[PDB]
Length: 58
DNA sequence: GTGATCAC
DNA sequence: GTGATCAC
Image 1: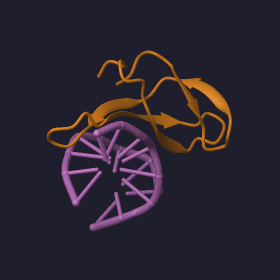
Image 2 (image 1 turned 120 degrees about the vertical axis):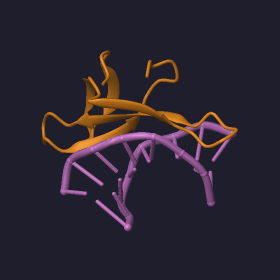
Image 3 (image 1 turned 90 degrees about the horizontal axis):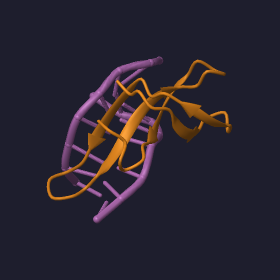
Image 4 (image 1 turned 180 degrees about the horizontal axis):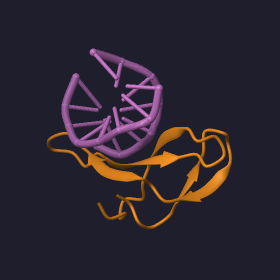
């Protein structure tokens, strides 16, 4: 569960500040990987994933 | 190619 | 079972 809002571009193309429903890190052995959040487009109700800032707490 | 996640 | 999310 995320808490702080994230500036994302939604699939519908708009700039939004959304609270991710789930957050996690995806990274292979030996490498930094990326932090990802699961978001819900409030305008379409559809789910999408988006990169999180590197210092976003998991 | 590899990592995690889950709506679909 | 996978699309799609990114960085290395």
